[PDB]
Amino acid sequence: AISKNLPILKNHFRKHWQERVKVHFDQAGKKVSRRNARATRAAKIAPRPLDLLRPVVRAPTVKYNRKVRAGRGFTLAEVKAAGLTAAYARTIGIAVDHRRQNRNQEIFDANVQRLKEYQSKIIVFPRNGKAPEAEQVLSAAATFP
Amino acid sequence: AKQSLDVSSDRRKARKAYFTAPSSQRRVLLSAPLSKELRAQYGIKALPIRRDDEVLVVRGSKKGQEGKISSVYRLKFAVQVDKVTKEKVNGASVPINLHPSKLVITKLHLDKDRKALIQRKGGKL
Amino acid sequence: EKAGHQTSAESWGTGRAVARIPRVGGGGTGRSGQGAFGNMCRGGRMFAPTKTWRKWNVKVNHNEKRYATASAIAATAVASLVLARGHRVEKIPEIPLVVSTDLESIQKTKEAVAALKAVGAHSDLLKVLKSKKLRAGKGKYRNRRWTQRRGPLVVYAEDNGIVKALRNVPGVETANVASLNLLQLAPGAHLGRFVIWTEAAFTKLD
Amino acid sequence: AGVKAYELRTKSKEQLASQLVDLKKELAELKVQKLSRPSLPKIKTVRKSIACVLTVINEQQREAVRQLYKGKKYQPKDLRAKKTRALRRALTKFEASQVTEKQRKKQIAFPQRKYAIKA
RNA sequence: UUGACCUCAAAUCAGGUAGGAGUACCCGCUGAACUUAAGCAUAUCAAUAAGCGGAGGAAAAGAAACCAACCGGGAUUGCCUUAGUAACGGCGAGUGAAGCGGCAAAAGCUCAAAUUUGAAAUCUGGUACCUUCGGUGCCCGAGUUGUAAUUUGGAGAGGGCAACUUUGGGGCCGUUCCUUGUCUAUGUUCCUUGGAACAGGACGUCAUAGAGGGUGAGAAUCCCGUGUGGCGAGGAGUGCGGUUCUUUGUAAAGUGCCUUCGAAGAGUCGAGUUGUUUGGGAAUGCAGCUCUAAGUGGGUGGUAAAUUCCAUCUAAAGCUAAAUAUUGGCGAGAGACCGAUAGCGAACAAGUACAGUGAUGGAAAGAUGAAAAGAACUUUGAAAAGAGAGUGAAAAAGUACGUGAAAUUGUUGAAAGGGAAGGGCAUUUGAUCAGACAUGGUGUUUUGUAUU
RNA sequence: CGAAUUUGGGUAUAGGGGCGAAAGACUAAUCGAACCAUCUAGUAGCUGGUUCCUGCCGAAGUUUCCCUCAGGAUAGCAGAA
RNA sequence: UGGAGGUCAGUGACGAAGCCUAGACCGUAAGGUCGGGUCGAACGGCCUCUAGUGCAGAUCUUGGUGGUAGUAGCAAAUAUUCAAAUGAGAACUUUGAAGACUGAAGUGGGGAAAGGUUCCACGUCAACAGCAGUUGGACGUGGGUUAGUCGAUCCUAAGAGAUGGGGAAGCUCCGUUUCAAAGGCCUGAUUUUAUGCAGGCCACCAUCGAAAGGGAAUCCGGUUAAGAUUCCGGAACCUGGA
RNA sequence: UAUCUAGCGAAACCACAGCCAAGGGAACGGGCUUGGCAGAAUCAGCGGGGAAAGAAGACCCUGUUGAGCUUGACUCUAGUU
RNA sequence: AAACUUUCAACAACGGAUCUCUUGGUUCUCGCAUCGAUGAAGAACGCAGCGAAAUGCGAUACGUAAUGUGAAUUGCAGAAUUCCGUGAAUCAUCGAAUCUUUGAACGCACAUUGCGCCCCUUGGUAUUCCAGGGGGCAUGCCUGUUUGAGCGUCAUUU
């Protein structure tokens, strides 16, 4: 059972593990299905940017303190500072976080400036217009890195 | 060379569809474009296939033999033609099977539903 | 997973003058009392049944791939390796054969075959045409009925009908310079693929 | 040859019932003759003829009741849409699309605005 | 005396719903042992098998009584990673997560508890009508022990102060789209072999079609089909330029400043104990029992307990697509898979036959030939059949049918043999057989003189 | 061999259960715990088997420890690089 | 050895693969090549890839086949024989003549359970009837089972088992009258009328469980290839019904 | 009955087989060594031998393999108190 | 010398290996969401000119109707210039129907083709008996409707 100089191993295969084995054969298949779903989804919202404008955010722990990343949604403080309402923003693709707070000015300004950069670079069609199609971009994240 | 994902190049599935064919796959389309006497003279081409056509056997041991289709044996995947028969040993004469693909249609058996395809295609004769 | 185990066979034990292999119970069938479950048994389970979690794809270092690709492109310009692959380049005026990028915009298959005869590469076509033969073995009814040689590899910078014009040309493969598969550049790990470059594809290599 | 349904649909109840009786008489007569002779395929289309007459008779009777209950709820279950038990129990298009007045005033005020990013 | 109300009942009262099936995946309950530990009891197997209840195309989960401790993230799910790690374990055998990070997909919310009280504004059903997935009358009702409007913690409500937006269901052109139809390229030209050309050779054509299949052998061109496009039929679709069908009446919601307030879920939380479970270890979850709260309260902050803070969220109520699962169903496309003792048990009238009272058990069995042309006819025989004959490219294909091995058997014929046979080296005898002075002095005297 | 008799059909009792004038008897040729399927390809230090050729090298049954004594680990002996 | 990539523009219906061959050659060998025969559609060499890759054994698996061996044997139940006919064919089939046996708790005549068409007729003998077969419970094709009275049905028996209700996570378990709001027939009425409306008695509590228990009522004679207490001819009975 | 005949027609078993004596050998050989010898094909019997066949000894031991049964064995447990 | 084991450029057997074939399986991937009290899944019995099985179907029974295509089906037959057409077909569709006995299975019962009750008819010159045709009669619930019950209770005192 135990023999010559080898590392002691822990291979957890004493249950009926062979019944719960998943081979990801559909890696290529899932990727194709995902790109199709992205393709069809973008068509249905044809002018819209296929994503919500996400905010900038500092990563939690002391390990990732140095990094800043894309969060969930804009704080209601940030949205009011821009000049909008959460009900309106959720309709023009600016994701809003009610649980988030701002306890830090640089995140506050960087998110507000992100908002003004969004407004100046997007055009909202009136509900009774002529729909002047405006060369949709599929990524709001790539539009505002 | 095949492109669409709806067409299968599976030999197993193809012969299964061939032998278990309904009229959608019950041979070719069974209606199919004709021989050169009608094709080369006019140019306005096509007309469907029927029983009482006349044909010329262009291949086989009965090659170069003429007659009328006595029956289109769809189940047996062959057409029977009168005057091309096997003489049995007892004097009986049984009709010999023959595949339409080894035939050319020499004289058609016309009807309205043929002349509908002429209008549908745009022919003038 | 259940092949050969869909039975309730049990061993008779010793004392009955038969092998201790499990046997089907019951009676009145012919199957009753017959050996089961064993890789030595007719109708039993095979030894170490094949599994889907066998390793199928094998990872190759990215850099080694591009190393082998560069070796395959480099061996393209070597005449000796291209003849040794059997690529009928005796009538080709020079190798690497590079054509003007008009062939990149050819449209009909007639002028794809016309271009091959003009650059001298059509001898590779007659090779593929006459090297069609039935595959020996059971691969015939696994949708692999025929085998043939490979022809020249036409490499282009832009697709302006080149792929369509050459699609129905047997053995001829087309490829964009961006990809340049090793699977086509060294077919069967044999170096020296006959490549016909368009001018623009050639200059993109730098 | 065999009677045609498109013909029978022009005939009234008494004509069809009379047409049915002498067909059943023809079938009954044919079954007697089935014993004397080995084969008689005529019995098949007579059964088809009997079936054709009954098909149209049931069709007028079912159609007669259909506009008898027309325009009012509670048609007979045999007349109702068969589609499927779960589809039959599913919420209607009107009922599934119902919203509260609270939701209605929010949907009106802020619908999903159509826009696009330019640069 | 006569009417109610509450509770309870009855009717083949008027109209409905549930039950079973399948169950691959999914949500729960219930629940082993073999096994491993080289014994075995905790452990492990396994919170598995078996058992029971309940769904959908997904289910569950889900918009924090969260994670954190940071310069903070911000519903849920899933993948990569964290990680065989923290941790649990006769600390043995073994077991074993989560936060962060990257990504896929991302969507939000709504009830209870509020001060309509100048008007129950609310809803089912019955009848009536209509343009029937419903609208409008009217009526009986239900309902104030509370049905509407309004608010949901991200807020909100009352009151005082402004120059701000929207009045459309299914159509029809059309549009991922669902089910489908139809039209759209080129040799069967000539010689050889053969029964059959679909083989060999010569000469062509088309190719955005040289996939696949069929046809009497290996067929882009005999056909489809394939490839490109074209023209049509019906359908859950407001996404839009319009809608044969008004162009809505003294209303809907959003924002700024200032005052007052601002309900927020109980035999529940929480505590003890027990059992079980977990990596959760002075107790991770759950459950039984006992105890039983509160409002700057409560929960959480992974070592039990006072005291002081701090950081976070807001339970005991509720809905929600996507990414995620799927050995079942339906429909498709494939493979370095198997090839009839293989592959599913079943390629075939296979869960058929057969066995067992029953639960249940459960096979074997694919190939004439291109076509049946399935052997007409004559003679022997009671007949089966034989011998001819005939069909076939082949009866060395006759249905006891492609090929037709071996064992075993009748056994061209040869040989050997006094209680086995077979074997090794060697020769002899018998039988049988491969290999050799065929063109190279004359550069050639005969020999069908460039055939030497 | 007129009875604690023999016996048909109906009915009841079902597996650690039944039934037993008691033999561990009987419970469908199964009984000191039936039969069927599944867990389950249960585990086996034990028995048997383990499929081509040639070339080169070539052992051990000894040490220590082990509920070790028909087994392992360890060292030795051997091959290969 | 099976399959895969590449190549030999390899072999092949003018014959691939397979198989047989005390024919040849090569290799120490694993094996390779070839002559001859058989055969009919595919298959090889070389460079590589890959694996369900090599058998004499496992009381191995499945299948097939020997020696034993024309052997053991085909001897319980007293027993057969003669002739004819039918048939190629008779020890065994039919007919006659004998001889025997069951000897009325039968080798007789009926039934129950079970079987399921074996019944009966006609053709018929490949297989089955451990010899035989012209015969048959065999084979093929058909015919046949006639009820108010014979049974079931009805009744209850040991006992099964719903509801009411109570357990049980639950498949389900108990429970059978229990702590339940468990009930017809006469001129009531007797002309929007059949319950628009004062006409009594209750103290019923499901249902299933016997083809031998209890029960309404049928006999004789005749009839068929096979049915009969059922058909037919006579002669009766019982129950219900104005 | 056996026997012989006509029909019908198995099985067990079987590495190969089947004459001895001694020897030596896994210490009782059909085979090996040395001798004796040894002549086709066979039939009915027969029970000396084939350490005959029938069954992976049921006795005995070993296994860190069981089970039935019993108890002040260890660990629990329905019930009961 | 025969008769009696071995080898066959040998034939014939036995047997079914090998080879080649494959309308099957297996595995992978992709898309979809639809069983049943409007009676499902499943079972039994039947149904064809000539069917036993198998497929399909339900006494309208290998099938009716509606639709498309446009001459079959085919083992043998059999209505046929049914064929220039509201039209063949073991054809495809498939929306309208039929859909026996059952089964969650529903009047009660069920090893019975058992036994009832209500409504409308027809007949036997009959509200009650019998027969025939057609309709019906399960539980648990929910919402509503009528009829009630209870000194539970309110008005309300002949």
Image (cartoon, coloured by chain):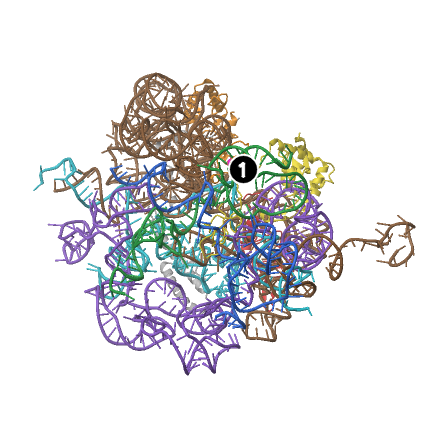
Chain colours: A orange, B red, C yellow, E brown, F green, G purple, H blue, I cyan
Residue drawn 45% across and 53% down? C25
**In the rendered image, which quarter contains the C terminus of chain C?**
top right
In the image, residue F27 above or below residue C188: below
Q: Is residue B30 visible?
A: no
Crowding at dot 1, Cα within 10 Å, few <14 / some 14-19 / many 20+, comes out as few
Q: Chain of mark 1?
A: A
In the image, residue I85 above or below residue A138: below
Residue F55 lies, in percent from the top left, at 68, 42
Q: Amino acid at mark 1?
A: Ala
Q: Main secondary structure of the magenta part?
A: helix
Residue B12 lies, in percent from the top left, at 56, 49
Residue D82 lies, in percent from the top left, at 38, 48
Residue drawn 45% across and 18% down? A104
Find residue I11 and report its image quarter: bottom right
Q: Closest to the observer: I52 or C61?
A: C61
In this image, C149 relative to A139: left or right? Answer: right
Q: Secondary structure at mark 1?
A: helix
In this image, B10 relative to E187: left or right? Answer: left
In this image, B89 relative to E67: left or right? Answer: right
Magenta span has B13? no
Residue E53 lies, in percent from the top left, at 35, 43
Find residue E229 and report its image quarter: top right
Q: Which residue is mark 1?
A: A28
Q: Is residue C182 visible?
A: yes
Q: Closest to the observer: C113 or G144?
A: G144
In the image, residue G165 above or below residue F23: above
In the image, residue C135 above or below residue A11: below
The stretch in magenta equals: A31-35
Find residue G5 and report its image quarter: top right
